[PDB]
Amino acid sequence: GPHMARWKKAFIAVSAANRFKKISSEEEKRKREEEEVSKGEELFTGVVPILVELDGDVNGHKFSVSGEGEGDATYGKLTLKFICTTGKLPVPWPTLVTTFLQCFARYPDHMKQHDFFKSAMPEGYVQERTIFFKDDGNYKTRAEVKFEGDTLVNRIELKGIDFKEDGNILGHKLEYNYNSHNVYIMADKQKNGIKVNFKIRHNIEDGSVQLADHYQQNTPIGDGPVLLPDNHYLSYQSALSKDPNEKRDHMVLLEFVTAAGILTEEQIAEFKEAFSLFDKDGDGTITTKELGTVMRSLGQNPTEAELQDMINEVDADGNGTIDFPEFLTMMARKMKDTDSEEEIREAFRVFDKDGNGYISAAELRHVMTNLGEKLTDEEVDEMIREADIDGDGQVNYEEFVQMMTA
Ligand SMILES: [Ca+2]
Ligand SMILES: [Ca+2]
Ligand SMILES: [Ca+2]
Ligand SMILES: [Ca+2]
């Protein structure tokens, strides 16, 4: 009847007290994450030296490539030189361009919250691809991109299979050039990373085009937080050239890369019932003294500075006290340390004064009195008798859970 209203008012007040106790740590965690996802981009404000190492095996042709150069994310510019250290490449240099550093993309200011790549640094990320050459074979690559000292290093393994002996790749029919492409990026929340896809068009000497379908996943190497982007794309342009002083099989690569492409009315009255237990003098604001009274009435004993720390997190407008909108906000906040259960379990422990697993009538009477929820002895007995299913005259946790989620 009127009895779950009395349980609910007490439960919300206790929950609000538990949220006051927890709010400073929640806010620290949130600010710490924002600070941590923002540090990686600071590593890219100037020119960054780059090393690249690849070991490859295409149709049983094994080879290795070494690259060096530098990247400048302020301009979205990469300049690299690659040398085949095992002789001549068994595949055309242009088929390896995508495999040979997306942390150097220029992200415009209003998009900087969508730059996964830099946010993963310096610990770095793994980049995995399958590249399907239409009517031909496929590459599978795995790359670790990370800082080693002040140098950004890209270490790559590549495996190619099913290529045709006389196709465009093993027959070396690709022109030594490159076209512009858009690289489409979306968040992969399950893996704390991104999923990427694009199609490369390689010019063939006879005027046709060889398509190369790219599928890509990037996952952070470290355990820290990363930026998970909204859907967007990177605009890529690439130019291939040769070093006229260079005898070994090699490629000079220039890339330019820029990102683009981006309650209940009764609940309010319930909350107001809980708010009045804090606002002892009914003036509509909770002071540190009132909050301290509530905390002590619930078995805590915070210092004046702890109380101030608590009010400071919730005092959104800064007048030094807490009003109902500010109280409302705190209760609407979704916490990163709760399921449905944990709020209920924390509240049950306040009611169960001695922590023996059962709320007795004497305990309920005592906490109600301490909170100032004005109830007679008979009304407390009614609340117990209503929640009590097994008839022991006390409320265990399971009985409490049933009542609160009813
Ligand atoms: Ca007050
Ligand atoms: Ca205020
Ligand atoms: Ca007890
Ligand atoms: Ca019982």
Image (cartoon, rainbow, N blue to C red):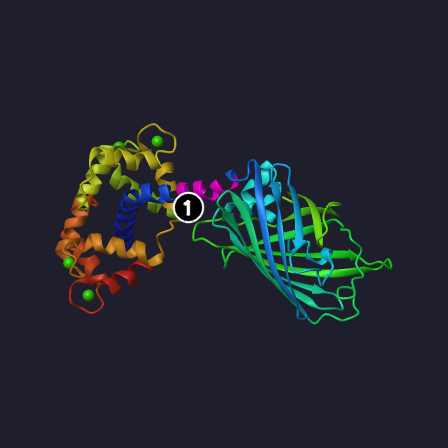
Q: Position of residue 321 (x, y in %)?
A: 30, 31
Circle 1 SS class: helix
Q: Which is nearer the eye, 33 or 247?
A: 247
Q: Is residue 54 left or right of residue 164?
A: left
Q: Residues within 10 Å of mark 1 (few under 14, many from 20)?
A: few
Residue 220 vs 325, above or below: the answer is: below
Disc 1 CB within 8 Å of nearest ligand 2 atom? no
Can you identify the residue that label 1 sits on? 265
Q: Which is nearer the eye, 353 or 44?
A: 44
Q: Is residue 128 left or right of residue 375?
A: right
Ligand 1, by image quadrant, is top left
Amino acid under label 1?
Glu
Any part of residue 280 in sight: no
Report the quarter where the N terminus lies.
bottom left
Please tell me whether residue 36 belongs to the stretch shown in magenta.
Answer: yes
Residue 396 vs 17, above or below: the answer is: below
Q: Position of residue 302 (x, y in %)?
A: 20, 39
Any part of residue 156 in sight: yes
Residue range in magenta is: 31-41
Helix, strand or loop: magenta stretch: helix
Residue 191 vs 181, above or below: the answer is: below
Please tell me in which quadrant of the rendered image residue 319 appears. Answer: top left
Report the quarter where the C terminus lies.
bottom left
**Residue at point 69% right, 60% down?**
87
Please tell me in which quadrant of the rendered image residue 94 appears. Answer: bottom right
